[PDB]
Length: 98
Ligand code: FES
Image (cartoon, rainbow, N blue to C red; front, side, top):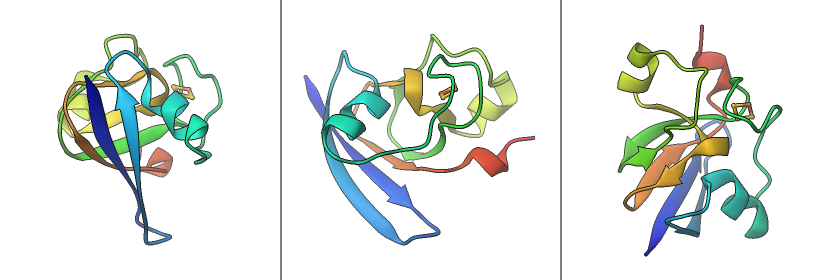
């Protein structure tokens, strides 16, 4: 399947829509589709690529940085996240973490 992924940058007031394959990470699809997003490690072990779910689900089983509570709050590491439904997510949420 292929899911619609809506990227929202609150500080910039932008809204971009991308199509992501069930077996591709969100960040990868975003770049291919022309949207550069923040990143560093690309391996699920930092917070640079952090985003926050507005709606929808992801499988980020490969991440390791976020604790359970943060996940509960809706945070996602875009670099290692696969969409598991259509999703609406806020990007550039790195600073929200502590
Ligand atoms: S860039 Fe480091 S966890 Fe995604």
